[PDB]
Image (cartoon, rainbow over all chains, first blue to last red; front, side):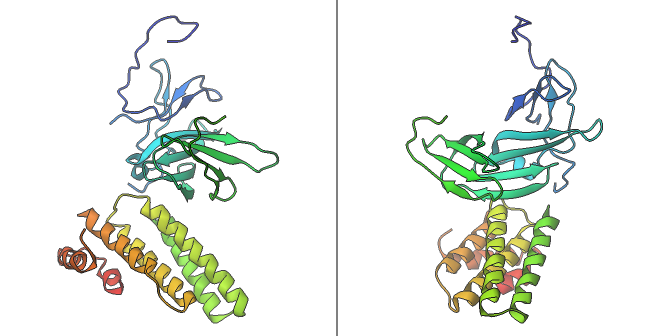
Length: 162
Length: 124
């Protein structure tokens, strides 16, 4: 239900999960997720332009191998080569791994200390000292480097993070 | 993507052989402990996948290179290498429990099913 609409709209397509959602340049509103092997272009994960609009991409999202493990997604940048598109996007898994993807190219995997990661945010922290800040259901958390997918600190009990 | 991991293996093995042939006492161990961590990270990335029949002949390759290079630099073995081998074999089985002796019994019957990675198994 949107403000500007005020109506209960149903999603036409039949998905399992909506690992990510949000606004992108040129598109207005978007959901990642799936419907129902080592080729980058296979991907197993439908974009969907919201309001029963186009699937929009089945081309350069993460491989289907990862599709069995990934629990959460967090996009970091969206470029458009032609009608197609190119997203560089972070995932994380039930197997305590944090992965980078560039056009669905698995690059820069790290292995997390703790179990059942929930979410990730991005911390700027000056010039290029960029950290991915990972939460867990276990009420603990990681701050992992960018540049080098490498654990910097891993605190515990952490009622909340901001 | 197998190609990428394969490429990485290739690259780092060649880098290790280069350190083996060329290099000074410090620079040798520098490139070696570089390749070591390359192979660690690769291991962890592949250990992040479920099973993958086509991956195992690589993973086992990788673990073998890892252990060798590990043990070669240590100039000696450890029990982490037993656990490494433990993990590799357990992975082999979890495609298709108790301890190394019964694992190997079940493993080698699992190899008499004829998956073509015996080259690796016999190296293990």
